[PDB]
Amino acid sequence: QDLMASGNTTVKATFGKDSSVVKWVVLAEVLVGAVMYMMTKNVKFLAGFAIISVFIAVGMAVVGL
Amino acid sequence: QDLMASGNTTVKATFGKDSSVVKWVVLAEVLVGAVMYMMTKNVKFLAGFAIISVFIAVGMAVVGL
Amino acid sequence: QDLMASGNTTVKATFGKDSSVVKWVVLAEVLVGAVMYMMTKNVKFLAGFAIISVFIAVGMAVVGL
Amino acid sequence: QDLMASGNTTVKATFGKDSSVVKWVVLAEVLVGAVMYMMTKNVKFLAGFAIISVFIAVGMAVVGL
Amino acid sequence: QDLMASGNTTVKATFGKDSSVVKWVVLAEVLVGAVMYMMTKNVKFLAGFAIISVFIAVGMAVVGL
Amino acid sequence: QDLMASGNTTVKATFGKDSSVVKWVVLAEVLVGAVMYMMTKNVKFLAGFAIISVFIAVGMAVVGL
Amino acid sequence: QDLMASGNTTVKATFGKDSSVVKWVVLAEVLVGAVMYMMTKNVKFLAGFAIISVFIAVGMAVVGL
Amino acid sequence: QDLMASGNTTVKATFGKDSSVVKWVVLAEVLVGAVMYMMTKNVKFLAGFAIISVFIAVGMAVVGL
Amino acid sequence: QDLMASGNTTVKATFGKDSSVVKWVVLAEVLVGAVMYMMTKNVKFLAGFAIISVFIAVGMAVVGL
Amino acid sequence: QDLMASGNTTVKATFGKDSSVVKWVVLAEVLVGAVMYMMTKNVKFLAGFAIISVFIAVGMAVVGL
Amino acid sequence: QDLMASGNTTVKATFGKDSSVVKWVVLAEVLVGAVMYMMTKNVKFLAGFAIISVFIAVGMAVVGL
Amino acid sequence: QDLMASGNTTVKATFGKDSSVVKWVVLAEVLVGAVMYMMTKNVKFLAGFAIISVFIAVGMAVVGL
Amino acid sequence: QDLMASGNTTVKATFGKDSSVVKWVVLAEVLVGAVMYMMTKNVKFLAGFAIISVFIAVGMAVVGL
Amino acid sequence: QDLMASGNTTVKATFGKDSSVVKWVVLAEVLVGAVMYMMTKNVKFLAGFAIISVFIAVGMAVVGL
Amino acid sequence: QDLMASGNTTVKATFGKDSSVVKWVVLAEVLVGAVMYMMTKNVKFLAGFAIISVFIAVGMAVVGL
Amino acid sequence: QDLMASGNTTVKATFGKDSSVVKWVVLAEVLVGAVMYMMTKNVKFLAGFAIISVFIAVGMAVVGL
Amino acid sequence: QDLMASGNTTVKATFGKDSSVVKWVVLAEVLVGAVMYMMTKNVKFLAGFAIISVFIAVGMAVVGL
Amino acid sequence: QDLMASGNTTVKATFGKDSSVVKWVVLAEVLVGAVMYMMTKNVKFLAGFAIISVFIAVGMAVVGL
Amino acid sequence: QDLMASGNTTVKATFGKDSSVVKWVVLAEVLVGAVMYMMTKNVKFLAGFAIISVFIAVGMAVVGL
């Protein structure tokens, strides 16, 4: 029949590829990496900056409801 | 005779390989891992991202009602 | 529907390309590098000085809500 | 079946032979070597300048998704 | 009888000699080594570039499900 | 008499020298080591790659039901 | 709306182009270089003496709140 | 898709063939060589003076974004 | 009809965006973070300082009776 | 109506920009940093010395009842 | 009203510009630096010797209850 | 009132300009320098021999409880 | 009328600024800190040694019956 | 009246400036420091050796029942 | 009265200037230093060899029960 | 009474002036020095060869249980 | 009378100077040290190899039922 | 009586002078040293190669059940 | 009885005098030495080229299972 947890899925809107929360993540990510680099002065922290984004993309693309 | 817990199995629809709940899981999984990585900056948390999915797949394939 | 974490986004104002916090970062960055150079006397630490800025720019441009 | 990490591969676009990041690398490479030479006045640092490029090329050619 | 963890093995597809993830690895490997060399200017980091690949190959060949 | 936990031993099939799970192990082992080496650039992590395998072999040979 | 970290910016007064701290830096810089030269007797250490100053200037000019 | 590190490339403006930083380099290069010659009185240090410039040129021409 | 828990909502006045309690929170928040930093000397604890505020704002804006 | 937690706000007097407690903080802050420097002999710990103060200022200015 | 942590401030006497503890600090500071120099034979450690003192002075002057 | 860490100051006697410990320092200082010179045969290590002494003197004179 | 818990207040004598118990506290405090330092060899534990005392003083002064 | 915890104060005899326990402390202190130095070969651990003693003295002098 | 931890003080015999344990210490001290010198070939490690001994002596003389 | 760590002192036999371990030391010492000299071709490493021996002798003579 | 835990003391046989368990210990001790040395390549781990043995001996000699 | 851990001692066979495990050790030892030398190009790592063997021998000879 | 780690010893085949891995080693050894010589232009790095081989041989001959 109907799976009862169905409907809704503003969950998607909530978490969607376009969503506040998503944008939140990389934001602080951008920060801390930039932060960390001051401390470290190593080239490390600029990756998931891009990577998590596409990482986000793929899993979002993977699941995407 | 008839096992009384039988019938129904919208349970399947509820939990099925295609189900809201399933999609829910990996979603937050994608999140927390991405979250964690900001904190950790270790390559760890991108696995069950894929793995749980196929892990889901196999057990779902294992049982599948 | 409406993703509930939406609205607000003074978060943007908070963290925006024009924001206090942003300006804070490079500031101390300028400092420590200048600091470090006294100790090191190597040409190293003048990079993210510029780079993080454009690094900031791109990610800000990348996400930008 | 389908390997779940598949799809996406804007990763390629991200890191591709033509990509920002790639161009970033050799850039600073050009710099530091030129920098170093001032200090050293040895003929050393002009190599991966060319070499890393073809080094990039080969590995890119090696993997290339 | 049947080992229950059997079946599935999109795990293979997931991790196979041809898989996204595999290609991911050497990619960043190519990067960091090229990165490192800028810092170090030592001939070190170009090895697993090739080596891990064949290292991958052998273990993949070793196990290969 | 008969030890009641006897019979079954699809447990063997489950965990046997030929089993999914076994193959699973070394797989991720191959990964993480290759992973680690990127970070470390030390020759460390290629051992149980082979060793655990024969380690597996011996204990499997040791017990083997 | 209002970014909450805003206001204040005695931070500027604190770190400004005219600030104690700024003047502190070059001071010790002048010292150590003069110090170092006694040891080294190389012409090295008189640079950021001027350079960091304009380096300070530019980044200060770059950010300047 | 779009490589996320793309856009921006004021990086170019930052580091471009016409850029402050570039001009900075050869400047101090001119200095130290002239400096060194006083000490050495060897004809050595007038090379990258010209050479690095064309060296700059070629790599800039090589990459040039 | 009338929901009996209705009326009142000095609850709002009690907890409102302008309320004692709200102001209480960030206060101690400011403290402990400043406290923590003495111990840690890490840049961590200055976030919800701003963030919780806008976090407060949004949820307050979200619900707001 | 009246939010019951209102009134009082000797809380302010307690924690105010002019308050014992506030002065307490930076005090020990001054200490430990000076302490730490003996151990470390790094230029690190003289920041929140000033910074927390203005950090205090801003949040105090942010909330300020 | 009255901030309850007020009064007392033998805390000042305890930590004041004239206080045992203060004098304690620089003392050991004088020691370790002199100690360190034996090991290092670098001119480093004679700074906060003077500097921390005025550093003490300023923060003491900054807060000074 | 009375700063509680006060009294005592056999601390002074302990560390005073006339104290065992003080005399200890320069002693080993005399040694290692004399030691070092055998190895180095450079005129370096005879300084704090005198200098630390007056360095001791001044800081002792600076603080002197 | 008369608050019945009144009178008595040998409670004061019991707990007073001059009381056994009070003296007990700092005593063991002196101990454990001295103890801890052996283990830690960090400068930490000598504070409430003085501080709790004045902390005692103030609260005693705060309440003082 | 009489504070009931009063009398006794063999507690003093127990913990007094002359007491077994006191002597116990510095003893092991002497040991571990001497121990540590073997491991470390740093001049660190000879301090509270003297210092804790006078530290003991002062607090003992501070409280002293 | 009698401090209860008193008596005994075979503790002294245990740890005394003449004791096994004491002799143990310098022994291994002699070793490791001699050991270290092979590795280092620096004149460092022959000090507490004598020094700790007199260091032992003084603290033993300091406390000596 | 009897110090409990007493007796035994095959420790002496273990470490004694005549002991395996002692002889072990100088042995490898002889080696590495001879080794080092091949590399260095400096007259350095033949000292503790004799010296450590008498160094051993004296400390052994110093302690000697 | 008779202490009831008495008799038995195959406990001795169990744990005696000659016992399996004892021999077990040093065995693995020999191993791990040899193991560790591969990793470390420091001369550390060959001590309790001998030492624990005599350490065993003494305590065994100390107690020995 | 009989020490219960007795018997068995295939433990010996397991770990004996002739045992797989023993042979395992030196094997990898041979490897890593040979490995290390490539990196180091120092004569270091060929020792326990022989030494651990006799080290093994002696402890084996020491305990040998 | 039977030492359980026994059997197997494809370990030998794995690591044997004739084995891939062995051949791997000297290979890269040949490389890096040849590499190094370009940099160094010293006759150093052609030794273990031969030496490690016989070094391999002997240890292999030493252990050889």
Image (cartoon, coloured by chain):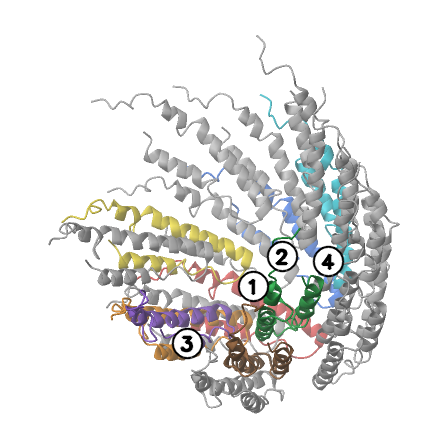
Chain colours: A yellow, E orange, F purple, G blue, H red, K cyan, Q green, R brown
Tell me the subunit letter for badge 1.
Answer: H
The image shows residue F50, relative to residue K38, as above or below, that is below
Q: On residue H24, which mark appears?
A: 1
Residue G65, percent across and down?
51, 45
- On whether disc 3 and disc 4 are found on a single subunit, the reply is no
- The local secondary structure at tag 4 comes to loop
Question: Which amino acid type is shown beneath numbered disc 3?
Answer: Val
Q: Residue at image x 46%, y 51%?
A: A31
Tell me the subunit letter for badge 2.
Answer: Q
Question: Which amino acid type is shown beneath numbered disc 1?
Answer: Trp
- Residue pointed to by mark 3: F62
- The local secondary structure at tag 1 comes to helix
Tell me the subunit letter for badge 4.
Answer: K
Locate residue K42: give its quadrant.
bottom right
- Residue pointed to by mark 4: K44
- Residue pointed to by mark 2: Q6
